[PDB]
Image (cartoon, rainbow, N blue to C red; front, side, top):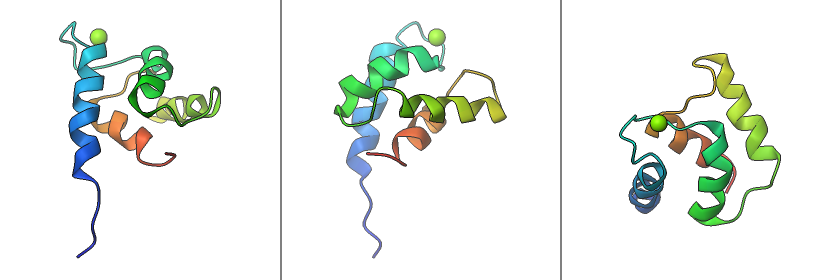
Length: 76
Ligand SMILES: [Mg+2]
């Protein structure tokens, strides 16, 4: 019934962390481009950007493992 992909969640967690080991729980749209590519190597090089920009409609350049996953769930 409605099959998703609970596997990417595990890989993301490691990427969101492997990049945010500082123990902050938040990453800057900067690492993303680098974490997004090393995470699946599939997005563009200026589009994932527009996404991390839309984020500004709430926090302001800071994504939580939740947005991180919400930003990688759209384009893949
Ligand atoms: Mg941090």
